[PDB]
Image (tube, helix red, strand yellow):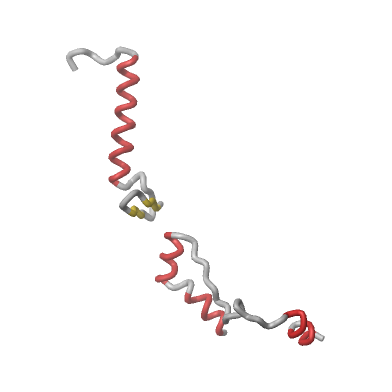
Length: 48
Length: 48
């Protein structure tokens, strides 16, 4: 719900995962990890 | 009636939001904490 960080304090009544400073980080890591797996299986085409 | 009023004041919008951010510990005591009154006597004798 709430989180205190280094210099900043983030509070949401619902969730912090839906807060942008987090949400963007979560979304970026989720996709970056999924592609890495796709790359490990070689499913990534050279001309994409 | 006095103590009831003290309990409602914790239920006010101001102190409600305070509880949402972090647990609120309220002392509703009348200063019985720094009391130097000896309970071995003034309580027992009262009861006796």
